[PDB]
Length: 352
Ligand SMILES: [Cl-]
Image (cartoon, rainbow, N blue to C red; front, side, top):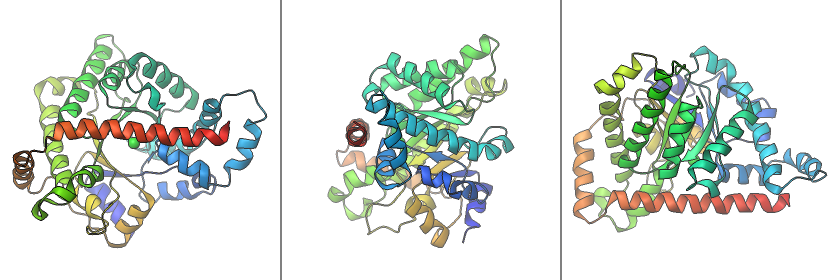
């Protein structure tokens, strides 16, 4: 039942909604969910393409914007920023009630900037300013350029959602870049206590990529095993003396965010990823249908840290079979950028 969302909160995990649309906000639905266990919102270009195509409340906004001398991209941004700002205002009470630790809404920069650190910084700074809300995060793909940009944006005091992570190595590089940005601010005597960063580490896409050629003992196991090991990396990084010195001065840890947590194979229980990845100081962003399933028949237990030994043994067998999870991760990141760019192009065409 719905109290499962407060049980998960008590176990230390935030549940966010992996969807956004004009009607979600205008109807009052988002506000009601913020009172009843949902703590934040994520978007991406695929989510906006579907929203723009399906939600009748955009039609008049598009008609209005087609009266103006604006590029399709700016028409998109006007729409998307307005949805995000409004969602931020819905989430603000929640955000303030936790000292700015929850209640965030994420907006992604243009996918075509993904390998351009400067351009990414410039767009992220602009979108942060355009939204004009303390509880907005700018979402940036975790390419090498993205991690360069992360360090700059953190040093600028901007909260960031680093996305399309599939790699423990690339996640650790992101933590080190965050720590450099924080340290720069502390040395400059600047505030860091409200800067928040999440690392959106994708789940179902790993299983989708591998399962058809894995032996049955490993099917549906790899993504969770990778996440479990990533969380152990996280504990080790952030408890080390180097970070503890920053946290003592008010720095926030980055938090892992489980993304792509809808189940994509009907052979697996639809609550598999939410049920399996609950642990303290994490986020899980879930699509509507998965939130529904979790409320109906999910389980709230501290599962993320259970059976780490077996996670590691399975990752050892994945390697034994010849699957290089770093190669896989890079491929998945590149495919995810291509797909987001496809979605973005599809969104823009009706705005010409
Ligand atoms: Cl995303």
